[PDB]
Image (tube, rainbow over all chains, first blue to last red; front, side):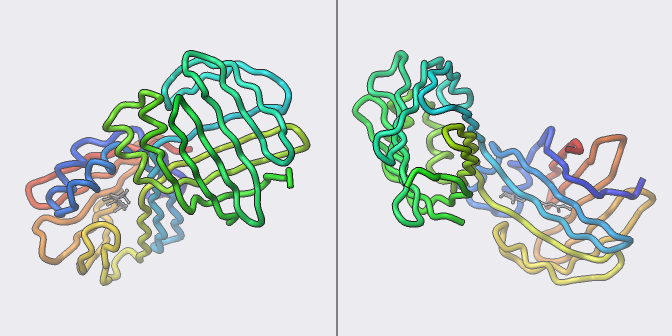
Length: 133
Length: 133
Ligand SMILES: *C/C=C(C)/C=C/C=C(C)/C=C/C1=C(C)CCCC1(C)C
């Protein structure tokens, strides 16, 4: 078939590094690129093609109900089991992940059109700010 | 407020390295992660949350008509101009990218539920396989 329409998810990628080196793509970029999954969206109508390639490293999906403890396997992060509980403290959503790691959890809250997330583990704190699309 | 619904685009990310290290995420993995932009999709109904964070690197878009030569600027790849021409050889879609690099182009074809993409540049060949979602 000549019909290449569809949404296509990468299954394998052989010698992407060699090809990128031939193009002179910088080292930093290649090191990232080889690790990414790619998704390809092809819109084909007769002889007209629109091709969109997107690259992704890892996803993280978590579902929870506030006030309901749950077993959480942090797959594709550090791969541990923790007992997670998310509760409200004012308008701050607060998560504690009980497990091997001390002081593990997070805080997530809104101010104006921005979302603030503070991730904690051990004595380390990571602070992230998101803007609404 | 407590409504955190929406699609959220990361604006900044402080000490992500510190946090991943405390989690014992491996060095190479940390170095890729710190570079990527994240998008957070939150679906909230009352106290029920579904959270999906996606880490992404680059995108590449190209539109063309089979048989019509066009100037391709490879923005976000090697940032060069090639005169690209895409043609059919049987059921294989074949592009030649004429410019500075020799043997530059690609081939795309369907076999079953799979899409095959061979990318070439200089003495290098990259082979990719995609499955329809
Ligand atoms: C017909 C479909 C084509 C030619 C798809 C081409 C996609 C690439 C040549 C991949 C480009 C990327 C890199 C070279 C590194 C950054 C990540 C990508 C996937 C955008």
